[PDB]
Image: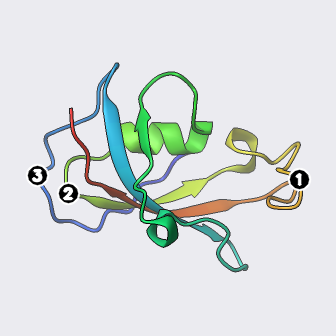
């Protein structure tokens, strides 16, 4: 389950498609918890493509549901990111995930 809560500005029309490499300034957040990940810190804005299952399932569906210049607000369920396993030391099992996502892409 991906729930988009959009900070408006941008275009609203340029949607990501297959075979397109897109550029995202992400910033993670734990529900009732601190930060755990940020692309703003390294300033390397995480170039990745669509449809190769490189990212987790919750981040993948919210990427296509944005457009150029926009700023969404993800809410990833535990069963789509890590909630059974949990990433060791970084993500606990049965975790609900929040992401500050900006789509400033190409292609």
Would residue 65 be seen by someone viewing this image from the given angle?
A: no
Task: Choose between 49 and 94: the one closer to the eye.
Answer: 49
Q: Position of residue 39 (x, y in %)?
A: 49, 62
| Of 91 and 6, the residue lying toward us | 91
Q: Earlier in the sequence, mark 1 or mark 2?
A: 2
CA gap between label 2 and label 3 equals: 7 Å
Quarter of image, res 25: bottom left
Q: Earlier in the sequence, mark 2 or mark 3?
A: 3
Residue 23 relative to residue 36: left or right: left
- Residue 85 lies, in percent from the top left, at 88, 43
> Label 1, label 3: how many angstroms apart (C-alpha)?
39 Å
Residue 17 position by quadrant: top left
Q: Is residue 37 above or below residue 94?
A: below
In the picture, measured across the screen, residue 73 lies left or right of residue 89, that is: left
The residue lying at 23 percent from left, 46 percent from top is 67
| Residue tagged 2 | 69
| Residue underneath mark 1 | 88
> Residue under circle 3?
11
> Dot 2, how many residues are within 10 Å of its Cα: few (below 14), some (14-19), or many (20+)?
some
User: Where 21 sits versus 66, above or below?
Assistant: above
Query: Are the two marked residues, 2 and 3, in contact with CB atoms closer than 8 angstroms?
Result: yes
In the displayed structure image, the side of residue 46 where residue 72 appears, left or right: left
Quadrant occupied by the N terminus: top right
Identify whether 52 is placed above or below 35. Answer: above
Measured as percent of width and height from the top left, residue 93 is found at 88, 54
79 sits left or right of 29 in the view: right
Q: Quadrant of the C terminus?
A: top left
Which one is closest to the eye, mark 2 or mark 3?
A: 2
What SS does tag 3 mark?
loop
Dot 3, crowdedness within 10 Å: few (<14), some or many (≥20)?
few
Of residues 48 and 10, which is closer to you in this image? 48
Mark in the foreground, 1 or 2: 1
């Amino acid at each position: 389950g991906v729930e988009i809560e959009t900070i408006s500005p941008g275009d609203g029309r340029t949607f990501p498609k297959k075979g397109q490499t897109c550029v995202v300034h992400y910033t993670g957040m734990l529900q009732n918890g601190k930060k755990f990940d940020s692309s703003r810190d390294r300033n390397k804005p995480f170039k990745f493509r669509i449809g190769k299952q490189e990212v987790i399932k919750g981040f993948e569906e919210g990427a296509a549901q944005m457009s150029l210049g926009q700023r969404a607000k993800l809410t990833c369920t535990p069963d789509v990111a890590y909630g059974a396993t949990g990433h060791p030391g970084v993500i606990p099992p049965n975790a609900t995930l929040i992401f500050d996502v900006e789509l400033l892409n190409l292609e």
